[PDB]
Image (cartoon, rainbow over all chains, first blue to last red; front, side, top):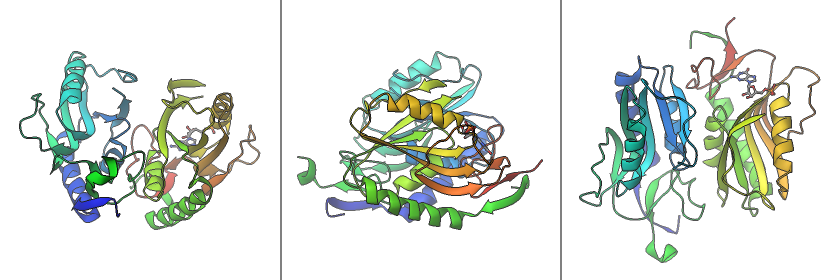
Length: 164
Length: 164
Ligand SMILES: Nc1nc2c(ncn2[C@@H]2O[C@H](COP(=O)(O)O)[C@@H](O)[C@H]2O)c(=O)[nH]1
């Protein structure tokens, strides 16, 4: 907590936003038996918290980028990619391009955070976004620094003095 | 929720147990920088909830397997590392017995098992050492809190029995 510069969002903020996102996703996916792709290892906290509010049939899958590909054939499937944060958009840009060639019925992105770096280098459509954050080192709620801080029940900023 | 024959443990029971387990784990793993392996997908809810209570440096890793086919192997070289396997439920013990044999060959410094549930089926086919266990469950099909049936029921905030 001493290494934390300031808190951007508290646990109450986080849970309220997750419930809102879940309701929005339910509106579109409830009837679609979507493949909900979790981008390991960063998106896990967000992913499970979302799944705790999705009261319908869905098929989990995981990807690491490809090091680990998808176990499900996504052709003709409604697919949702769950990500922790989008910075420049490079990874997502290439991810979507790859996945789009597999011919899914639909493909959308849901990210916990979108880093405000102004105009991103890659034009990535973000359909669902939890929060827009400052261009700083984000820490807490799954975000780590040297495998530390993931347990903090907030989304905050790491002091520069800690990593520089 | 109407497909539940009955609830075995509510969210309050689960959360209390997780805090107890986290305290127990900290005792041993605090200064060990362990590799905490989550056996996806069922164990993911339990896994992330535990990690929210672990206030020390640790390295997450994930494995996807079934009894033994490993669809997604570890990213981490566990040679000389302290390793904890986080599982959802141990039934006959076959899956964990094979997983442990595979992991022990990689030469970890230590290797322990943490399971959310242990299904009481009497003498198991394999004598799997369980170091940490959340609850002993009866010989029925368990549903909820990560446990699914045909890709349904994971979101339930309780651990319960699937109706016949
Ligand atoms: N959802 C759910 N999965 C179960 C149940 N019992 C065992 N499994 C799954 O079967 C495996 C354990 O079986 P074992 O190899 O011990 O017989 C684990 O993958 C576990 O998740 C149950 O009652 N409910």
